[PDB]
Picture 1 (cartoon, rainbow over the protein chains, first blue to last red):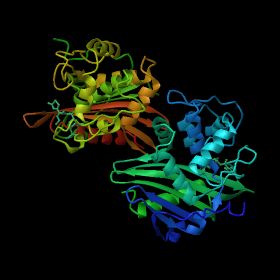
Picture 2: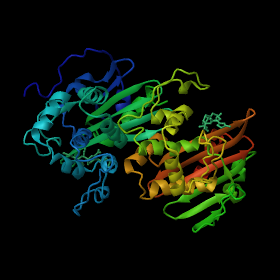
Picture 3: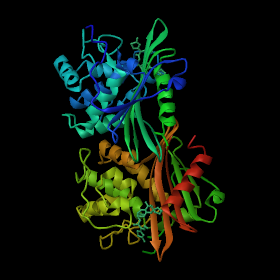
Picture 4: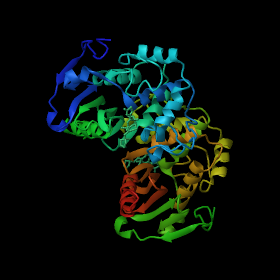
Length: 251
Length: 251
Ligand SMILES: *[C@@H](O)[C@@H](NC(=O)/C(=N\OC)c1csc(N)n1)[C@@H]1N=C(C(=O)O)[C@H](C[N+]2(C)CCCC2)CS1
Ligand SMILES: *[C@@H](O)[C@@H](NC(=O)/C(=N\OC)c1csc(N)n1)[C@@H]1N=C(C(=O)O)[C@H](C[N+]2(C)CCCC2)CS1
């Protein structure tokens, strides 16, 4: 418990320390990036990057994966009916498929998936995935400012590993997941990712943007965590991109 | 044969006649576009648009569809080994999957698919799809400046129908095909398409760009054919986009 807020495991890869404090501006947090080609990490604010926070809606990545893996949703049909309950966001108040669910961060879609998953499966997956503190707690919205916590550095390690390694997870699962995460594509690059936002007492307190970039030459996994300032998922995306552009990943 | 060079069937939809001769410049051809929402067509140079030409590499769209439909390739694996024969283009001289095959217009990939398809299946599909003159001839590269011919107007009608109508083609087939055709994506739109280029006596003679656009509000099917000037698939793409941008489809 006293070491379950911190990822202490030393890196067995080359790594560089960046200074993107100018881009982060009045916001506080960290940025991590992995380069498939260099098998190397690029970290800004490694202290913050090793502190564990709740994953918020970035966990939807893994919930989506579990749902595909247990045939809750599939490639032929991932649709779910709206229950006719009003939600704060209009995009939630309609039928969803994985793509629309993921793109609009429709909580109830993944909640409905979460309810059909046994706890021992979830716990087995987190173990094998090395997902943060691996702490399910009461097993009720555990990924939402609750027991489960992961570090910015681990977000990149766990995601890259799950996607790139020969897991029990199928290639078509990974591709379907990957489809649901595609944000931008042009001649130069494909950008994939997922935002996370936390709100406490009407104040943003926890902002994620986790994803990856495919170029012609390389492939990159990355994540931005915001802890103070204006720590929203959107602000995490904006910062991620201007860092990726200024580092010449998006050109 | 005397009516097999022309699509004469009258339109049972609204349609408008455009003037994009300025964009076409010193190139000659036509542009067709369909709007799901308006159930209406937008044609420039309807004469040219009704004349049938060989589909070149736009036929790869349908070959890809057939290969998925006959489990020649799958969502799990669509890879094919290179035979270690040199090809004029370097991107051809390696392993391919559907995406790389389609993106680089790797002829041999789809030829290898074509060879495993019965003729009566092909002929059945063209019948049900209303693909052009439906003429297979000797059934050997019939889609390459040979017997099979389709009009710019039909490219849009046949593609839209195959994709949008509940035929025997599965949703996952269509999505996998759709994935292989994605070119550009941003906040505003997803652009999908396939180029075609013909070369005779070292001169471009036949240029295609067939595809569709998904926006927030609408969905559009489109095609550009170039018959004279500099009629290359790439030039057909450039013209398609300038027309789509200037019509405010890519905004
Ligand atoms: C995942 O982060 C989701 N977030 C929430 O449900 C929470 N607050 O959102 C207001 C939350 C969970 S526990 C807690 N204390 N707060 C959804 N995802 C995001 C996201 O960043 O993708 C949302 C924010 N967006 C989508 C709203 C408009 C732009 C960003 C909120 S819902
Ligand atoms: C499909 O159009 C393919 N084209 C060809 O094989 C032919 N010529 O290519 C030079 C061809 C077939 S019959 C005939 N008389 N000529 C491939 N697709 C394209 C394409 O546009 O996707 C290629 C052309 N590009 C990529 C290079 C220059 C313009 C675009 C050629 S191979």
